[PDB]
Amino acid sequence: QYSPNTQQGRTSIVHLFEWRWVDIALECERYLAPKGFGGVQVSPPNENVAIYNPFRPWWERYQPVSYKLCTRSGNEDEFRNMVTRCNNVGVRIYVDAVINHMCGNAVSAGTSSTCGSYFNPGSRDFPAVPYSGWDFNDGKCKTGSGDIENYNDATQVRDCRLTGLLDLALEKDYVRSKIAEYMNHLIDIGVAGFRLDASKHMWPGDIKAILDKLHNLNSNWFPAGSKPFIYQEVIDLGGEPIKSSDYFGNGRVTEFKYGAKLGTVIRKWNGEKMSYLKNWGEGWGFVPSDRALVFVDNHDNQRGHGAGGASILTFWDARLYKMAVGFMLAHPYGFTQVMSSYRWPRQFQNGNDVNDWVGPPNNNGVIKEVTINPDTTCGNDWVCEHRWRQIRNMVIFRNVVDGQPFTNWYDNGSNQVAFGRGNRGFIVFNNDDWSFSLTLQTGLPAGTYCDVISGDKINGNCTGIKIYVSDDGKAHFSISNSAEDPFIAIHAESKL
Ligand SMILES: *[C@H]1O[C@H](CO)[C@@H](O)[C@H](O)[C@H]1NC(C)=O
Ligand SMILES: [Ca+2]
């Protein structure tokens, strides 16, 4: 469960946020597989509530109505077709599992579902599963509002409604069975793992009970005895009753301190400088590397809905974003997840986006298909950060240096640092307010290397910058503080 279950070599997964099943299937064959991506995290594939006020927000997908594979991304057949085509190409699929709750208790009863299933939140009656009033913690919670009021109370945080979402009683074998039945369906279809949404709101023991009823990965693509990869969404920063270590027994956990910290350092906020990254990792209070799932930003905190706050770097800050992601992909700590999102009309009104709810590109509710431009970029407002040369080439970098030790670190004491990975890769950063010109020991074999940030290597020709490594692994690097991308990266596979 700690093993991603990706093909040998592939070291990253990408979140194709709100993408359609059919677009993902194509992307797997036309780009993800060839560019070395390890897998894809998909948006919840089960039926959810169709919220029309605001108009189809992205967060409506976190309010389940049933476990039918019927959403705006596609139906069961399209979902199945996607898993098969991606697996057949070596790209794994990880599902965002919303098993801690159902829909809002204040939501109106009826058939406003992505699949037309009937539901009645008022009477806790979800016939498509089926679930009834006896399957919720309505009588287990103590709070006056029935919702979580005090996060210093681990109990109410687990038994009370998270912002009004109907809280399922995961202690009952019936509920655990219904959920496991849904998860086994996905496993048998071919998924390699799951993201356990809102894990902090579930008892570590209830989760384990559910994982105990899960089948092994499909023997057609995975070796016998393979267990699904498990990463739990636990927002744990500092001094909270619930520690992420409490979930180490079920699988990996999302390390939200990673992106929050990296964001302030790159932004150079409150005295932080890149030279401090010398001991990045557990040395900064992070969970053990072998239990961490890291990222710069996620669908939640990229729009202010998650931990990290204002220090979080997103595609909106392209220049600084690329460096942060470049640094994360080059550093050996944890398992990396790349973000892929869409553009929305950010309407900041007194320091808060009033349009952070806006859903994916759409035509009257119907999600717009992902178009590819001649320059390999996406249209229809899909950002496709994963298609950015600087990001995609760093994804490949991590694969190439997989297993190599962190070495040859250098820093000017401010914001000019560099380090290598064994003898397979080397990266240089310039985040200071002045040019960088110095000869450094890369620890790489002599030869001409293409800088994979400014360009690419194609049939023995570099389309960008070229670095020359001496017989003693030394090479000269020049980075202006005015450069489009103030960092250079070279590896064994970019050598001419
Ligand atoms: C790189 O490509 C060009 C043609 O586009 C060719 O003339 C040149 O010889 C190539 N160099 C190498 C080293 O293959
Ligand atoms: Ca709960």
Image (cartoon, rainbow, N blue to C red):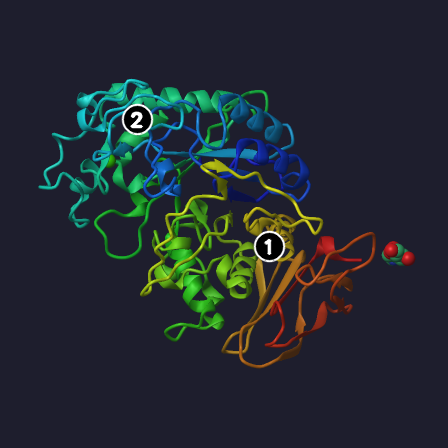
| Residue under the point 21% across and 39% down | 164
Amino acid type for the residue under numbered disc 1: Ile
Give the crowd class for mark 2: few <14, some 14-19, many >=20 residues within 10 Å: some
**Closer-to-camera residue (180/73):** 73
**Closer-to-camera residue (403/150):** 150
SS under mark 1: helix
Q: Where's residue 289, x and y in %?
A: 44, 50
Vertical side of 458 occupied by 233: above or below: above
Question: Quadrant of the image for the N terminus?
Answer: top left
| Residue under the point 64% across and 27% down | 88
Q: Where's residue 370, x and y in %?
A: 59, 41
Q: In which quarter of the image is residue 120?
A: top left
Q: In this view, does 368 lie to the left or right of 268?
A: right
| Residue under the point 31% across and 46% down | 244
Q: In which quarter of the image is residue 388?
A: bottom right
Residue 209, disc: 2
Q: Pointer 1: what residue?
A: 391
Question: Quadrant of the image for the C terminus?
Answer: bottom right
Q: Where's residue 138, x and y in %?
A: 15, 31
Vertical side of 127 occupied by 442: above or below: below
Q: Which residue lies furthest to the bottom in this view?
A: 434
Amino acid type for the residue under numbered disc 2: Ala
Q: Which residue lies furthest to the front in this view?
A: 364
